[PDB]
Image (cartoon, rainbow, N blue to C red; front, top):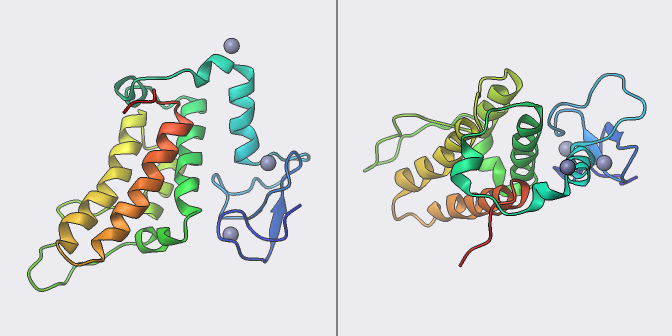
Length: 178
Ligand SMILES: [Zn+2]
Ligand SMILES: [Zn+2]
Ligand SMILES: [Zn+2]
């Protein structure tokens, strides 16, 4: 196995996947690495299994259909994986914890949002449809763009949103378009 966490790229107390060479910190994995379970398969492996059991799941889909899906176990897992892929980018640090807003010439957002809040919401089964999760994820980046206005720091929001959107289209097999 790898000797660094797949998500944060640091060593430490690592749990090793039994079906691939990836390793994780306990709370870097989503869901948090399960207490017992031998063998244990990571989220990358569990998502690969879904695909392999239903090859047709990789045919293209319309976003509008994906968003209306109820959060059954497979869609829960897909959203957990998508959230994890965002944490995998080091620029997610900016968006992880609860923000505050005190900048001359800007007003903070009406509905603040951050990664760790989405993570808690998924853990507590607060989303009933994929749309709930995706709306909160997109709101993170939209709030940032709006608040930072012409400051070059706005770009961090564009960058992390692009990671989110590419991974959303991959994980949920959104139909490719120009
Ligand atoms: Zn880690
Ligand atoms: Zn694995
Ligand atoms: Zn099938």
